[PDB]
Amino acid sequence: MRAVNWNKKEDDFSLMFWKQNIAQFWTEEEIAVSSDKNTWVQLSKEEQIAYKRVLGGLTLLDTKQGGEGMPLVLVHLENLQAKSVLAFMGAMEEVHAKSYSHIFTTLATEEEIDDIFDWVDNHPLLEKKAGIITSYYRRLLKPEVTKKELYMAMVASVFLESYLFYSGFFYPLYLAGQGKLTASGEIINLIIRDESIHGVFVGILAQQIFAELSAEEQQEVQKETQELLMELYEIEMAYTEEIYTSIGLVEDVNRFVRYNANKGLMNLGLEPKFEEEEINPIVLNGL
Ligand SMILES: [Fe+2]
């Protein structure tokens, strides 16, 4: 029945976000990465392996967001303009996921790349965090869904895009901020420019539906949000310990994770959970 009519606004922001999403369009071929080989080779074995691991985890999350997250969230939306922006955002998640293969092809050998993906595949923490987020999406695999089911999928999507990536983004930023792997750092920043607006946008949509829930549903959903935040946080602390102890950065990354959880909460129109904390300055420089 209904066709998208962009000459009549369905809300006050999808247009702005549409324009911004397309004005930020990019693909991996615009950033040559071969000059990062020079600094790559000067990384210790522990640093190389951490970089590869985090990029692997990043690639998984984008794989989920583009192939489950955006499609299952947008499919049910009655707002056809908003739905359009989210479709475009999904495509961009794939461009992101592919970017990381572009980085890998200059850095690593065939066999090394196989190893990265075998590792990401068999990883219990990555499996656990991706499955938690993704079960909210997969709840929407039925003909009709409630506002509350849709709201929690949106919470889960903002937690992925504004929060769960950042344990991974820490390290390429942290290397780039020191003039190391700067071309790959450039790509990661393009990805961040995108993820930043994705988190805002789906949070705006979440806040709209939140205002349409009953008082009772509002509190079920808030209790759920806090449990979900903290279920994810526990896994992130384990993740950060596994990945970063070898290179002595665990507590720096944890501060960064907490900071980005807070931003996720903010995007949802919610109050911070962790103490305000200064972010590592060399990652600020990498940004
Ligand atoms: Fe992404």
Image (cartoon, grey):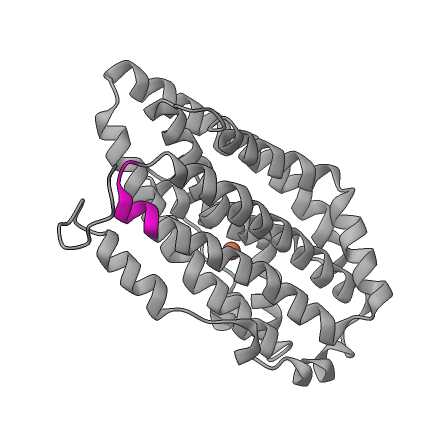
Give the residue at the far front of this rendering.
1
Q: Residue 36: where, in percent of width, then height?
A: 67, 80
| Vertical arrangement, residue 256 with respect to residue 23, above or below | above
**Would you say 195 lies left or right of 178 here?**
left
Residue at 83% across, 67% down: 110
Residue at 58% across, 32% down: 132
Residue at 54% across, 57% down: 94
Q: Residue 201: where, in percent of width, then height?
A: 32, 49
**Would you say 97 lies left or right of 160 here?**
right
**Would you say 40 lies left or right of 81 here?**
right
Residue at 41% across, 30% down: 152
**Would you say 133 lies left or right of 213 here?**
right
Q: Residue 275: where, in percent of width, then height?
A: 42, 43
Give the residue at the far right of this rendering.
111
In this picture, which residue range is highlighted in magenta? Answer: 78-84
Residue 205 is drawn in which quadrant? top left
Residue 17, visible in the rendered structure: yes
Give the residue at the far top of this rendering.
216
| Vertical arrangement, residue 232 with respect to residue 244, above or below | above
Q: Nearest the camera: 213 or 174?
A: 213
Residue 269, visible in the rendered structure: no
| Vertical arrangement, residue 106 with respect to residue 214, above or below | below
| Vertical arrangement, residue 260 with respect to residue 147, above or below | below
Q: What is the tally of numbered marks visible in this picture?
A: 0
Membership of 80 in magenta stretch: yes
Q: Residue 193: where, in percent of width, then height?
A: 42, 64
Membership of 124 in magenta stretch: no
Quadrant of the rendering where the N terminus is positioned: top left
Kindly report the secondary structure that dominates the magenta region of the rendered protein. Answer: helix
